[PDB]
Amino acid sequence: IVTPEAISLALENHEFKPWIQPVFCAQTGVLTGCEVLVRWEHPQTGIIPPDQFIPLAESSGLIVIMTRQLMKQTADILMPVKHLLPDNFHIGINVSAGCFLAAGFEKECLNLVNKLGNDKIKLVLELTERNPIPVTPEARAIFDSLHQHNITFALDDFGTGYATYRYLQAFPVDFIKIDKSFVQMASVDEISGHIVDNIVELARKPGLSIVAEGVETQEQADLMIGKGVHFLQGYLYSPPVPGNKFISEWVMK
Amino acid sequence: IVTPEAISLALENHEFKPWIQPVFCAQTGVLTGCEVLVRWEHPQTGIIPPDQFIPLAESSGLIVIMTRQLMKQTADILMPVKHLLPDNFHIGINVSAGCFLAAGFEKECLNLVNKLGNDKIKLVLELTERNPIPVTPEARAIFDSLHQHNITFALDDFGTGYATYRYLQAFPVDFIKIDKSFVQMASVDEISGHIVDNIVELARKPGLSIVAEGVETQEQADLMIGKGVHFLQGYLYSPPVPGNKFISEWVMK
Amino acid sequence: IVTPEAISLALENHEFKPWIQPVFCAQTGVLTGCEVLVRWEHPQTGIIPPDQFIPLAESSGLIVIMTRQLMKQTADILMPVKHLLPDNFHIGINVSAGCFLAAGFEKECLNLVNKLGNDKIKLVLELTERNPIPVTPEARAIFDSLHQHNITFALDDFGTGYATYRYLQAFPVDFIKIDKSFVQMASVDEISGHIVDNIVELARKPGLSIVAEGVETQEQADLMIGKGVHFLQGYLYSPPVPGNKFISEWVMK
Amino acid sequence: IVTPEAISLALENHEFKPWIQPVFCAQTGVLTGCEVLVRWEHPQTGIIPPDQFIPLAESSGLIVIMTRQLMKQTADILMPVKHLLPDNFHIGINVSAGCFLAAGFEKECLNLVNKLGNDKIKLVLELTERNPIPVTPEARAIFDSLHQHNITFALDDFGTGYATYRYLQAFPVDFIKIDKSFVQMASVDEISGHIVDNIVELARKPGLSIVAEGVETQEQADLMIGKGVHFLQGYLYSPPVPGNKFISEWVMK
């Protein structure tokens, strides 16, 4: 059904598309950036969602190709409209350890930034919780090198998987994205709200910015805003959308 | 060299001994409890340290036997002196998911507590970071059952492995033990101290107690005490010691 | 449900029993030996068949303990009646690569043979098809050592898994056991019968003996006998049975 | 060094070349066919041999692309000279389970055969021993479909990996290729020769043809010929060579 060969074939047939989800300033509601997500549109049978292919992409290693293509395609999509983007427009790309450590990764990040404007945009590498970067000198060298080139980092889905305090200690990242399981449970249960407060306090000393993921309702947003979260993202504002529709809805109007 | 069969044989030959490390009130320096640790004394060749056998104990499943024996032996060691123990004396036992989910686990915990005094002692199950308890109804039922019997829980080596905010959200534990990597780096680096502050703030709302592990120097202790940590443990006070020596040094004088 | 810890606990609780299946001379119908098989009798819920635990026993490594116990228990079962066993009575034990390479394996085989009579019995190590012995000098040394001690080898379930011509080339074994899938399909399909002929021709040059497994009907037996198979085993004669019943039915009458 | 991304890049840069090894009638020495093998010529550093990339091609799934390209390129190479090929000229292509089960496989095989002459050539899918086709109705349907289109099958490297009697039982193939480890050891050791005899007897009933692989010396050939092997292949006649050289040496003279 879903195999490494089917993923390879799908990459060659360009069936993996960059869908783009806007991200907003929590204070003002204004567009500040986006996240690039992947959708597999199988020509006959339809969507195969990330949950069914990403893991196998990761274990097979094909994720490296997929992420490279996605980065390239995102540059193509946003280049025509880059002069219309707000200043300091954030572009979130999901990065696993495999991609981060692969030969040629830094180069691919530079190509994206140079095409779009070294100083107009901010590339945010959203480090995944499943396949954490190893805590080694060589990993830290790649991390520092990218930082020197004004590329930034997020701990994605923070509070789940391997997204622990240790990653913040080993790597001075720039953003923390709060997993949706805390955003959506804050004020259903007894600790989730407290956990968000904790992530807010965590960020404050080193001066990191926080994004709440999975914001689905207005009460969730108000709650996140009240607690000092900096950016918001979720279905309340918009799900991820095809690039042309991202441009048409959120950039060019 | 180290195999599952060698571990089995070593269990039958009683080569795995409960060594006991005292734990202290951070405010006053007073003895409040202990942790039970395992040492493998191979008759010819000497110590085989936990790092070389625990993982294989865990993957083989033999850990369940080992932990059961350790619990039993700890009861035997402390029973003669239980009337000399301070009130609310804490006994820390390291528990993996495998042990926690095994048939007969709750019974073994009760046997320990009943032998030593339902109300004199407090059993603390120190949940490991490597092999986390699954987040399921059945796991939560076992957890709640043990709580109803006045047994308590710690997230051990918090901030490392799978010891994440999620575990605190899924399981209302009673203690957090701060991994030594934060205790010992707090005031060498730029975030470790901040991380300890964060763990202190985390605990405060639900009213959990914190123990700093790996306290090795007086400056580390002072630092942990100053930051509001409740209990201290480490080589500064004492390494783990054989039971008879634990009793002789810390209980019976 | 079935875990490594449950297998460990079951080993300690002696829930894994040696059941014994007789093996017969194809020419005469006479008892020539047996195979020792394992049955897990779970005290409440009943049988857990080999298909559900062996693989996990193998990957966890616990198989080494289980096989050792089975060998020991087989000696205990047959010792009281060893003087009643036919001469050259074969005892088949199922052995994986893990058991074969584990420290202490040769010793366990000798203990079995010495207890039962160096020259009355023939121990047959039935090498499994799933977890083949590696083709290395060290493996061959263990193999040769055991041969020098008059212990013999079978390629079990030959024609399936990794039970290939290569194993016969690397290890001069003494027996081939034909997988039941060929025995039972010989004269349903177009090649299975031909495959059995092939295994018979294979054995003839080096002078190996063949046992047909899974003999279920008289026509299957007649067919195997006609094709020059030396030994027969299967439900037609008897399924595996508890030891006491093996002794009572096949040895002591 | 060797990664899935490097393999992808190498495919796009056409660094994987079809080298072709002739195959001959054992009786007469006459050219009867060929096998298509892959060589990775890295532009700076030189050859990367199959042992270092095939496994990763297979696990990544990229093998499907590579095999497709190889099939296409083989058609291009032989088309100009197809009228010069002997009748019933065999073309051996190495096929793993992944390729065999991938969408579009049957079509690629037809394209090769139609380009070269439905009745001049015989396509032989050489099924690998490492990644066996699963024994399922759906696999058998694909197998039967290809057979109806006059495409044929070989069990490659028979006697090693998963190349067992079972594959012959599940799939009525047309050829068996004897692994070189038996060809080259026949008359060094005590069983290898016997194994070849066995493969010859195996083939005879269903009427399969045998090819001896890795024929390196004249004595190996004479031995294989004497034992009733139908086709020969190996360095004694020719190693694999670039296509142009295959055509120039073995077809066009």
Image: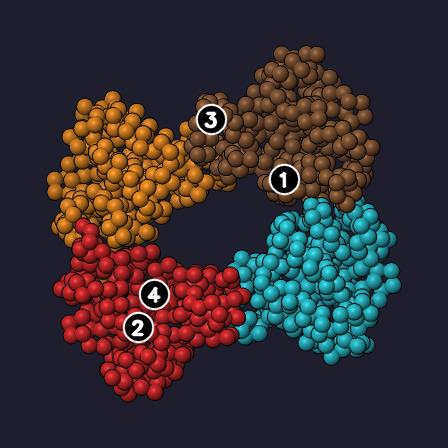
Chain colours: A cyan, B brown, C orange, D red
The answer to whether mark 2 and mark 3 are in CB contact below 8 A is no
* Nearer-the-camera pick, C155 or A80: A80
The amino acid on which the numbered mark 4 sits, given as a three-letter code, is Leu
Between the C-alphas of marks 4 and 3, the distance is: 52 Å
Between the C-alphas of marks 2 and 1, the distance is: 56 Å
| Nearer the camera: disc 4 or disc 3 | 3
The amino acid on which the numbered mark 1 sits, given as a three-letter code, is Glu
The amino acid on which the numbered mark 3 sits, given as a three-letter code, is Thr
- Chain under label 2? D
Between the C-alphas of marks 1 and 3, the distance is: 30 Å
Circle 1 packing at 10 Å, graded few (<14), some (14-19), many (20+), is many
Circle 4 packing at 10 Å, graded few (<14), some (14-19), many (20+), is many
Question: Do tags 4 and 3 sit on the same chain?
Answer: no
Determine the secondary structure under disc 3. Answer: loop
Instruction: Report the disc number at residue B45.
Output: 3
Residue that label 1 marks: B129
| Nearer the camera: disc 2 or disc 3 | 3
- Chain under label 3? B
Residue A23, percent from left and from top = 77, 64
* Nearer-the-camera pick, B104 or C82: C82
Q: Is residue D237 visible?
A: yes
The answer to whether mark 4 and mark 1 are in CB contact below 8 A is no
Where's the C terminus of chain A, which quadrant? bottom right
Q: Is residue B30 left or right of residue A138?
A: right
Instruction: Report the disc number at residue D21.
Output: 2
| Nearer the camera: disc 1 or disc 3 | 3
Image position of D138 with respect to C89: above or below: below
Determine the secondary structure under disc 4. Answer: strand
- Give the mark nearer the N terminus: 2 vs 4: 2
Image position of B248 with respect to A102: above or below: above
